[PDB]
Image: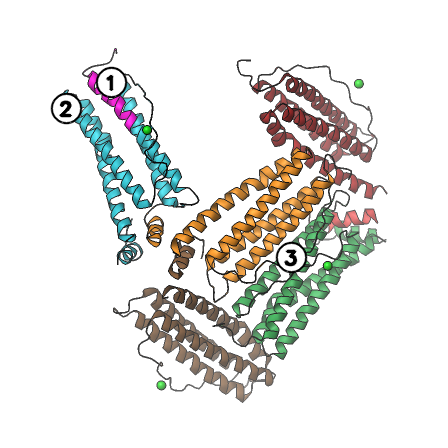
Chain colours: A cyan, B orange, C red, D green, E brown
Amino acid sequence: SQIRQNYSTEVEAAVNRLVNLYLRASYTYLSLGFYFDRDDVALEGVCHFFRELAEEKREGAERLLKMQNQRGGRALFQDLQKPSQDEWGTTLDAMKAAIVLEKSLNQALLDLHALGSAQADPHLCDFLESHFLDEEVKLIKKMGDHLTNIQRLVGAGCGEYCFERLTLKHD
Amino acid sequence: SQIRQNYSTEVEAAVNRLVNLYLRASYTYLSLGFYFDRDDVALEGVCHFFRELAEEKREGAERLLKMQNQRGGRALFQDLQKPSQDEWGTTLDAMKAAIVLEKSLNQALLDLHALGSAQADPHLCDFLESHFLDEEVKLIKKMGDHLTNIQRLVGAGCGEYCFERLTLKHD
Amino acid sequence: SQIRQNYSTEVEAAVNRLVNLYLRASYTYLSLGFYFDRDDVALEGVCHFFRELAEEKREGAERLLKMQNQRGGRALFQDLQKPSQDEWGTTLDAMKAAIVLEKSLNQALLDLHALGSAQADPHLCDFLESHFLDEEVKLIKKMGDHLTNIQRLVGAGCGEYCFERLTLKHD
Amino acid sequence: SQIRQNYSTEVEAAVNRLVNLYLRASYTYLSLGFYFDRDDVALEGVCHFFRELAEEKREGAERLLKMQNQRGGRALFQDLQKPSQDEWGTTLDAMKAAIVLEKSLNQALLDLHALGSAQADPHLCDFLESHFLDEEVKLIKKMGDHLTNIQRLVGAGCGEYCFERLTLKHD
Amino acid sequence: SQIRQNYSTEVEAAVNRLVNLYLRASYTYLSLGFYFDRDDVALEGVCHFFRELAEEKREGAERLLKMQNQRGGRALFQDLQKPSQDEWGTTLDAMKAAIVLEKSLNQALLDLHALGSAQADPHLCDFLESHFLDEEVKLIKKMGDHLTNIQRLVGAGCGEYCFERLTLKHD
Ligand SMILES: [Cl-]
Ligand SMILES: [Cl-]
Ligand SMILES: [Cl-]
Ligand SMILES: [Cl-]
Ligand SMILES: [Cl-]
């Protein structure tokens, strides 16, 4: 206001839309987590994996909102749509839906970076580089690793997984 | 006697019957535990799960007996029937019998709560709320989680369980 | 006022009356305690037992007054009548008067609980369940235990008491 | 089964009967303990003495059941009869009933030892020698010491007890 | 010699034969252990299980030899036959051979106990009771537990084992 400098209306609006997308993603992971806590599903480590991602996505939204105020833009909140499913199937189904969700967030980050670069907004571009882009690359790599392991188990694959788990040193 | 106040004969008798039910349940879990210690059954974690429940059910009976004396009622003991089976089958069979047993205890708790509420006995009602009702809900949820996991193993289910156990973080 | 919600005028008034009853009980225990400190009575453990109950009853009144303000009611104080006796007799006499007093408090608590339940005031009902009803049951049980022991001493009773005290392990 | 060696059917059955006797004794001590917790009885050290014996007798039953499985026999549970009394009288009455109960357990242990010796089962005989026979001799000696002291108090006896308790060094 | 008392020539000779049997058993477990260390067998936990039993059997022989000298008998050593097999098959085969071996040791212990009892040699009988008979019962029970678990794995059995291992608390 008194502080705003080199901060376009286009970036301000796109940051508000990205907050909605991150809060939507948090809501989707809340739903995924409670589905795996059902007594007829009962996969605690899958519950915990998704409930932690709910926290991460809400914290990403909060960092964007902090940045919006640091730049002198104004936070505007919209309705948050419910998640796409009420029940999430198997661990494989859920992990495939999570990779699709993370791809969509990553594309929105890349699109906002491109808008910042077009607007000659290096603070915005560095903010996304430093706090979001590598977090998404690392998370998508982990989900792809998980998908391969789940697929080799729900199809000699059982054997190779167990050897790697129970004989070889790993984190 | 000198102390009894707002404590109906109906509640006193129903507490003595519930002590018998809890001691019966303890006896049933003692039997379940030693069956899984047989050399031809030999599932130590299943033995330990049921022997711990024997302890919990006897401690529930002792808390009811303490409360009976705190209210000025008189403990009356009856014969304790032996458990329904001498041999308990598979872990799945045993877990299904345990859920049936816990449902029966929970219904007896709910029936005693309803009698206390009809008798306008808020101490009795709070005693059951505070020390029994949530213990039963949590235990039945755990047994239902176990049942789902055993069923997915003794039927891609083997795979999904092992992934959750050996890759994902859990308690 | 700005905060009051689901808090009936009937409960508000009954809480003010119960504060008077608890402060009256505190006054009665103050008197009991100083009577047992007289040089011609001189039972220090009896003095200390009643002076501690004076503190407990004043703290009960203060918790009710805190709750009255938490709900948006208004504390109203009335005159406090002096205790029923100036001299309290023997330890047996005093313990019998204390059980009568505690019965009267317990009945007033049960009556207020019944009014809260009729008014559909679950906060009030839980407040009494959580902070008062079991405190009274435990205290009345202790006083009844003491009465039995005093009676077996001021009447083979002397023998059985001393054996339990001096040979057997107790708190 | 796969493990059973030198373990007669006669010993197996007699061990199951002795488990019933020990669980019956535990039940009797549970009843004794809660009777001395009544507000009209109110002898805490007597309550604690019997509640500890309930624990000891159930632990004896559990050690027999463990041994039954170590030898390849099969645990078989029967109905547990209620204790012989609902009310237990004075401390003297209760201690006399406890000595009768312990004599009956000791005789059953001695009878099982004799059967093991006749069957040339030295593991069984040593098991009873090492874990049961001296526990019973020591407990019966303690109960006899208590009986003499209670008798000298509920009959110069009061004097001699108090001197021993209050002047002379003892555990 | 100067010390020998109540120690029959029959017991002395039978102790020397039992030393040979224990050293033979140690040799058999040495062979079992190195077979499971072969690169074409490669079951480290099975190797370690049998190499520890080699140590236990040699220590049993040494305790018998110490006792022979404590009683004034004279240790006499004989040739030690090689183990019955050069290759030991699967873990199941090996565990079945180990139970047969332990049964044979247990029978030799029971036969020596019977000879000591016939010779009225209570030191010998207690020595075997205290240091050997329960060690054998516990080891045979463990081997029977292992056999049942191996059989349920090399035949829903895979499932029940994994649940007990990976969900339930065990030592
Ligand atoms: Cl929607
Ligand atoms: Cl029955
Ligand atoms: Cl007055
Ligand atoms: Cl009976
Ligand atoms: Cl040979």
Residue picked out by circle 3: B81
Residue A5 falls inside the magenta stretch: yes
In depth, the one of A162 and D132 nearer the eye is A162
Q: CA distance from mark 2 to mark 3?
A: 80 Å
Amino acid type, mark 3 = Gln
Disc number placed over residue A71 in the picture, else none: 1
Amino acid type, mark 2 = Ser
- Asked whether the viewer can see residue C42, the reply is no
Return the x and y of residue A50 as percentages of the image width and height.
34, 39
Label 1 neighbourhood size at 10 Å, few (<14), some (14-19), many (20+)?
some
Residue picked out by circle 2: A117
Label 3 neighbourhood size at 10 Å, few (<14), some (14-19), many (20+)?
some
Mark nearer the viewer, 2 or 3: 3
Q: Which residues are magenta?
A: A1-21
Q: Image check: D118 left or right of C147?
A: left
Helix, strand or loop under label 1: loop
> Is ligand 2 closer than 8 angstroms to the Cβ of mark 3?
yes
Q: Residue furthest top?
A: A2
Report the chain holding disc 1. A
